[PDB]
Amino acid sequence: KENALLRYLLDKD
Amino acid sequence: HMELTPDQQTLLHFIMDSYNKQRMPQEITNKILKEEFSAEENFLILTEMATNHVQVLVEFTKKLPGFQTLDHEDQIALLKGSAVEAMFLRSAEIFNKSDLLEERIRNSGISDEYITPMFSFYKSIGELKMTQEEYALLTAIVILSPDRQYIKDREAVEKLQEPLLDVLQKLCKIHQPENPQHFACLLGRLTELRTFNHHHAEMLMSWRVNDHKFTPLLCEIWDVQ
Ligand SMILES: C[C@H](CCC(=O)O)[C@H]1CC[C@H]2[C@@H]3[C@H](O)C[C@@H]4C[C@H](O)CC[C@]4(C)[C@H]3CC[C@]12C
C-alpha cells in the first residue's frame, strides 16, 4: 500500500 | 466588524478545540534544551520533531468538521498535500513570539541558502501579527485545499473550505479593524506558502548528515525514496 503509515494514522482512533 | 454567526462561532470552537488539543512530548522538548549540539544530534532531533508534527497534524485534521465525511482516498491526498505548508505555518507561529531551536536548525546540514530565505518568510508571516485563531483557521484552510494534487471530489473539499474562509475574513475584521487589507495580506502569504513546497522538496534531495535516514513517516509524507 502507498503511504501505509499515513493510512494507519488516519484510520487509528 | 461583522460578527460571527452562532454556527460560525461553533465552527471556530471546534477548530480551536482541535488546534490546542495535541502538542509535543516533553521528552522531545527536553532534547531541544539539553541534548548535545552537533549537526548529527540536530538532524535527529529536528526530524523526530517533524515526525511528531505529522502525527499531530493528522489528529487535528480528523477533527475538522466535515473532514471525515470526505472520500477516504481524498482524505489521504489532502493530508499528504498539506503537510509541508502546515509545517511552515506552525514554524512561523513558533518563531514569532526558543532561539535554541533556531540555532539547531542552523547547524543541521541544511544550507544557509535555504534557511535564510525561509526565516525571512517566517518573519514576513510574523509581521501580520496574527492571533492563534488566525493561525488555526489558516492551517485548516491549507489542509482543506480543493486544488491539491490527486483530489477526486474537489467540489466536496470546496464546500468545507468556503466556510473557513468566511470565518477568517471576519476574524481579520475583528482582530485588526484598523487594517482593512489584513485578510488580503493573509491570502497573499498563502500563495507564497505554496511556492515553498517546491523549495523544501529541492532541499531534501541534498539534506544529509552522516548518511542518516529520515524516519519512515517522513519518507512517506516528504517523498524521500
Ligand atoms: C516540528 C516543528 C514544530 C513542532 C511543534 O508543533 O511545536 C517544526 C518547527 C520548526 C520546523 C523546522 C523549520 O521550519 C526549519 C526547517 C524547514 C524545512 O522545510 C523542514 C525542516 C525544518 C528543520 C523544519 C522541521 C520541523 C520543525 C522543527
Image (tube, rainbow, N blue to C red):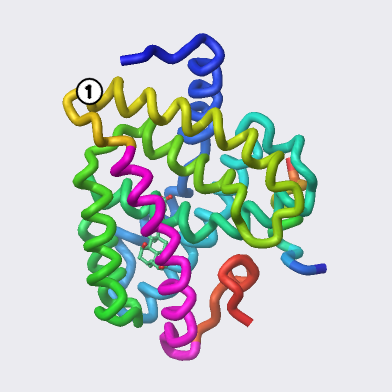
Vertical placement of residue A8 versus B5, above or below: below
Badge 1 is on which residue? B177
Q: Please name whichever residue, B224 or B8, is drawn nearer the observer in this view of the structure.
A: B8
Q: Quadrant of residue A8?
A: bottom right
Q: Residue B150 location, x and y as percent? A: 70, 61
Residue at left 55%, top 33%?
Answer: B162
- In the image, taking residue B210 as reference, residue B81 lies left or right, namely right
**In which quadrant of the rendered image does the N terminus of chain B lie?**
top left
Q: Residue B205 location, x and y as percent? A: 48, 85
Q: Please name whichever residue, B216 or B128, is drawn nearer the observer in this view of the structure.
A: B128
Dot 1 lies on which element? loop
- In the image, taking residue A7 as reference, residue B138 lies left or right, namely left
Residue at left 28%, top 74%?
Answer: B37
Q: Residue B173 location, x and y as percent? A: 30, 23
Pinpoint the chain carrying mark 1. B
Q: Please name whichever residue, B142 or A2, is drawn nearer the observer in this view of the structure.
A: B142
Is residue B192 one of those drawn in magenta? yes
Residue at left 47%, top 43%?
Answer: B139
